[PDB]
Length: 88
Image (cartoon, rainbow, N blue to C red; front, top):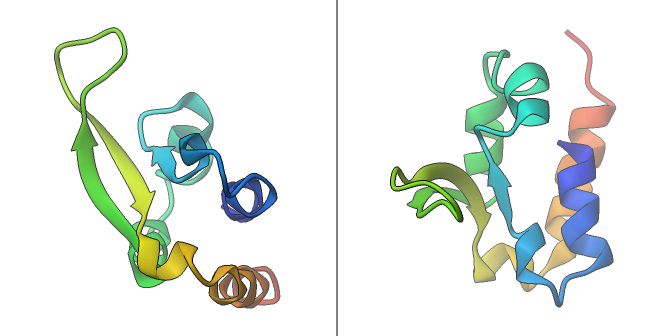
């Protein structure tokens, strides 16, 4: 999750880093298997949308960062640090 936020922060001019694919092997194994990760993405300014696939008829699930939060990367930087510094 911290890498997804750093990727859009490193290349904010490339829209391909605004959308996190929920069906990706890495996301599905590491993030989608946990409770509370979906709520975190929505809480820090991502919208849950269905986008057409580049090679399939069935739309896929993405977390897409809105312009409101993308315009102020400092909010995601604080949210990442709060998640990294947390304990059970």
